[PDB]
Image (spheres, coloured by chain):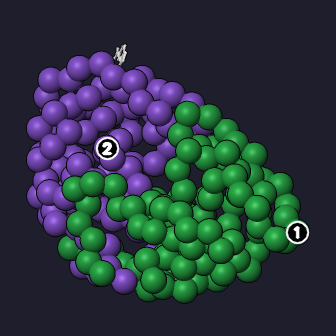
Chain colours: A purple, B green
Amino acid sequence: PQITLWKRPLVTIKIGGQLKEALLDTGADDTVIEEMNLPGRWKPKMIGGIGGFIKVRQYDQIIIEIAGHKAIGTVLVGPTPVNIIGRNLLTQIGATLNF
Amino acid sequence: PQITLWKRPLVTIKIGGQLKEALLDTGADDTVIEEMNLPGRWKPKMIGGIGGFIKVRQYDQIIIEIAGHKAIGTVLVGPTPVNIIGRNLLTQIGATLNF
Ligand SMILES: O=C(O)c1ccc2cc[nH]c2c1
């Protein structure tokens, strides 16, 4: 699809068999999803976030569906105020900026 | 142009007659530019950046060139480690996310 930026670029995602909405964020290196139960192994991590630093669970090789487009890659799970699709997954679905 | 996201989407900008580089950031509502002299009146805001909070000065009607494209809008000036072009300016240059 072609998504203009007149409002936040929010889309529907599927992750761990659950439908959520998420922000397509070209300024994020990584993908950060809200606290949820995920099938898969995780390792502990800390990342910078809104107003400070947060503990996250890093899940590698997660199947995630972004507006109908399949991606497999790293998802960070923790107390993010917004579900964020970062470049690690935007590259997998072939997302580009155009102007 | 059509910009892939394998690295951070950095472009050259021109603001206050100074050449800089900046991150095209679809996850940002606003534009945040590092400490610099803008010839205008301003109003103080706070923004929750990655790692903590900063105090910024809001400047309106700032003329800016982004990757060759002329835009006018609001810029927040403060101690940010990265120049951020947010949606308020990305809309002005006709930027879209495509996949
Ligand atoms: O999920 C947890 O219980 C947990 C505990 C500690 C850390 C440190 C980074 N991530 C964590 C997750």
Q: Nearer the viewer, residue A36 or B62?
A: B62
Q: Nearer the viewer, residue A17 or A85?
A: A85
Q: Residue B29 got which mark?
A: none
B36 up-or-down from A9: above or below: above
Residue B45 appears left or right of A83: right
Q: Which residue is mark 1?
A: B41
Helix, strand, or loop for circle 2? loop
B35 up-or-down from B10: above or below: above
Residue drawn at the location 16% of the way across and 66% of the way down: A94
Residue B88 appears left or right of B10: right
Give the x, y percent position of residue A16. 19, 42
Q: How busy is the neighbourhood of tag 1: few (under 14 within 10 Å), some, or many (20 plus)?
A: few
Give the x, y percent position of residue A48. 47, 33
| Residue A45 appears anywhere in the view | yes
Residue drawn at the location 69% of the way across and 52% of the way down: B35
- Chain letter of disc 2? A
Q: How busy is the neighbourhood of tag 2: few (under 14 within 10 Å), some, or many (20 plus)?
A: some
- Chain letter of disc 1? B
Residue B94 occupies which quadrant of the picture?
Answer: bottom left
